[PDB]
Amino acid sequence: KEFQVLFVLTILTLISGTIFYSTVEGLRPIDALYFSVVTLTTVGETPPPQTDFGKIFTILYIFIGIGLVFGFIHKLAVNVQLPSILSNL
Amino acid sequence: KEFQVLFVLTILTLISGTIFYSTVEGLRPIDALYFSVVTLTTVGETPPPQTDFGKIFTILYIFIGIGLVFGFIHKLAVNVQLPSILSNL
Amino acid sequence: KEFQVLFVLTILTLISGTIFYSTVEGLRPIDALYFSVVTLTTVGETPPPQTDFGKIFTILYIFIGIGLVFGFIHKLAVNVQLPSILSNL
Amino acid sequence: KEFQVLFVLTILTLISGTIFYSTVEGLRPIDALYFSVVTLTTVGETPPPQTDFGKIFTILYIFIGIGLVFGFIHKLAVNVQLPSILSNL
Amino acid sequence: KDKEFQVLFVLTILTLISGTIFYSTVEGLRPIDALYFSVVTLTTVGETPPPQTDFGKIFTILYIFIGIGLVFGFIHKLAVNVQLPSILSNLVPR
Amino acid sequence: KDKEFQVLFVLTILTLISGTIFYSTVEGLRPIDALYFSVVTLTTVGETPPPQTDFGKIFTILYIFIGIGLVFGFIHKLAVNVQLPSILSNLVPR
Amino acid sequence: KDKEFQVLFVLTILTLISGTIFYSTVEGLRPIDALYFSVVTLTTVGETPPPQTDFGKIFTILYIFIGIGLVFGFIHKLAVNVQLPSILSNLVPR
Amino acid sequence: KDKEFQVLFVLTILTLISGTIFYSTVEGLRPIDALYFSVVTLTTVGETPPPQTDFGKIFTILYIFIGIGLVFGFIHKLAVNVQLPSILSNLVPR
C-alpha cells in the first residue's frame, strides 16, 4: 500500500507536469513527460522553460515534487528492487 | 516554527541569488530566481554563469545554499505534504 | 560481498545503458557510457535523448538505476574510501 | 577536526579536477574549478567534456568525489551553518 | 512537533493511569506503588518484585509489549524536542 | 511490511515458547511464570530472581544475546507499523 | 563534537549528583549506595530494591523520565565519539 | 562488515571476561555467577542483587558506562548482520 500510494502520487505529479509543459511550453506530451521526469529527479539535461509562466511553475513544481519523487525512488529501491537481488544473493 | 525558519532561510537565500544574477549576470529577476532555484536544487538545466564573478559566487552559493535548500524540501516533504496524504489514506 | 554486488549491479546497469544509447541514439560507446553515468548520478550535463524511444528508456532507466547507483556511491564512500582516510587520520 | 578534514579532502579533490580540466580540456582554471564544483555537486549546468580522456576521468571523478563532496556539504550544514541560526533562534 | 509531544505525553499518562488502576485493583497495590510498578516496568528498570496473581502476570506481558514502544517514544521526543533545545538555550552566553 | 510484522511476531512467539519450555522444565517453573521470566528477561525489565541451576544460567546468557535483538526488533516494528498508524487514524476528526 | 561529549558528561554527573544527594538524604542511603541507585535506575539495570518513602517514589518516577534520555544520550556519544575511534586507532598496525 | 562483527564479538567477550574475573574475586562469586552478573548488568536486565562491597559498587558504575555501549553495539550488529540475513535465507522457498 505504501509503494502503491507513492507510485500513484508520482504518476499524478508527472501527469500534471506533462499536461502543463505540453500546453504552456508547447511540448509534445512525451517531451513534457521527460522534462517533468528529469527535472523532479534533478538530472536536468534539457534547456530551461521558455515562458515566464513555465519558469514560475517549474520552481513550485521542483519544491513540491522532488520530495515525493525521491520518496518513491527510495521505497522502490529498498522495498521492491533490493529484496529481489538480496534474497537471490 | 521549524518549517517557518527553513522557509525564511530559503526565501532569503533565493532573494540573495536573485539580486546577484540579475545585477552581475544581467538576468531579469524571474530568470535569476530560476537560476538560483535550479542550481541550489541541483536540477541545473540552464547554461553556466558568463562572468568570472558569477562563477565564483555560484561555487560558494552552491556549498552554503544546497544544505539549507534540501533541508526545507525535506521538512516540507515529511512534515507538511506527507501527513496531508497519510492521514487522508 | 555487499560492495562487490553493488559494484556488479552498477556495472551491468551501465553496460545496459551503454548498449542502449550506442545503438538507439547512435552514440559511440564511450559517450553512451558517459550519458548513462551522468544521468543516473543526476549530473546531467549533456543534451537530452533525441529519439522518443531513448526518451522513454531514460525515464525508466533513471527510476530503476538511480537508487542502485546512489547505493553504490554511498557504500563506496562509507565502507571503502572513508576508513582509508579515517584510520589514517 | 572532522569539518577540517572533510574541508581539506574536498579542496584537494577540487584542485585535482581543476588541474585536470584546465590541462586536458583546455579550460582556464576558474572554469575548470567550476566544472569540477558543478559536476561533483550534481548541478551539471555546463556542456560535457570534449575529449574522451576528460570523459573517462569525469566518470571516475564523479563516483570517487560525489560522496566526499556531499559529506562536506552535510557536515558543513548540520555542524557549522545550522547551530549558528539554531542557537540564534 | 509539539502536538506530537502533547499526544505522546497524553498517550503515556493514559497508559500509566491504566496500569495504576490495574495493579492497585488486581494486585492490591496502593495507587502510588502501582504507578511506580507501571513506570519502572514500561521503562525496563524493573526494581520491584514480579506480579503475584496470574492475571497480573498475563497483563504485565501484554502491557510491556504495547506500552514499552510508546513509553520509549515519549522519552525520545521529550529528549530531543523539549530537554535538548532547553539545554541549547541554557548554554547561550548573555 | 506486514509480512515483516508477521514474521517478527512469529519469530518472537517461538522464542518465548522456547524459553517457556526451557524454564518450566529445567528451572521447574509453571509455564505462566516461565513465559513471564522469558518476557521480562528479553525485554530487559528483569524483576524476577535469577535462574537457580547452572544450566538455566548458561541458557539465560545465550537466550539474552540471541533474543534481545529480535524482541526489540518486534517492539519497534509493532510501534511504528501497527500502533502509530492506528494512533494517527484514531486522532482523525469525523 | 567534543564540547558535545563535555556537556553530556557534565549534564550526566550533575544528574547523578542530584539523585545521590536525594536518596542519601530522603531514603537514608549512604552516598555510594545512592550514587549506585541513581546509576542503575537511569541506565535501567534496576538491581536494587525500590524506594521505601512515597517521596522517593514520586522523585524516582520524575527522575527516570527526565534522566533516562540524557543518560542514554551520553552512553551513545561516549560510544561513537570516544570509545569507537579509540578502538579504531587501537586496531591500527604499527 | 564481518571483521566488524568479529571485533565487536571479541571486545564483548573480553569485557565479560573482565567482569567475571572481577566479581568472582572481589565479590566472591563463582565464575558462572559472575559471568551472569556481568551479562545481565551490561544488557540492563538486572535480575540479581546489587554488589555487596563498595569496590564492587564503584566498578559496577564504571563497568556499566564503558560496557553498555559496546554490548548494545554487538547485539545490534549481531541482529542486523548475522541473525537477520539468516532469517531471510531461512524464509526462501526451495
Image (cartoon, coloured by chain):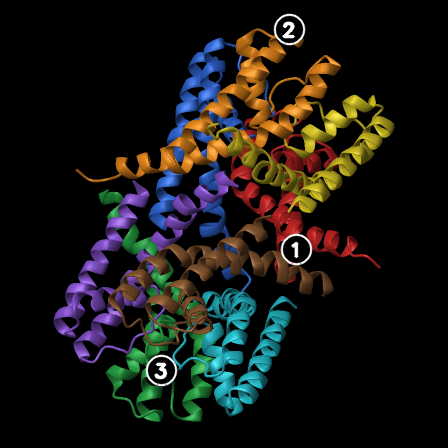
Chain colours: A green, B cyan, C purple, D brown, E red, F blue, G yellow, H orange
- Please tell me the numbered disc located at residue H28: 2
Can you give x and y, in whole percent of width and height, for residue C51 in the image?
18, 79
Residue F48, picture quadrant: top right
Q: Mark 2 lies on which chain?
A: H
- Picture disc at residue A17: 3
Q: In the visual, does A66 lie left or right of E12?
A: left
| Chain under callout 3 | A
Query: Split into 4 quadrants, where in the image is the C terminus of chain B?
Result: bottom left
Q: Which residue is drawn at 22% across and 68% down?
A: C31
Secondary element at image label 3: helix
Chain on which label 1 sits: E
Query: Which residue appears at 29% of the width and 49% of the height?
Result: C6
Q: Of H55 and G85, which appears nearest the observer? A: G85
Residue in front for this viewpoint, D15 or F64: D15
Mark drawn on residue A54: none
Query: Which residue lies under the disc numbered 1?
Result: E81
Q: How far apart are marks 2 and 1 (CA)?
A: 46 Å
Callout 1 amino acid: Asn
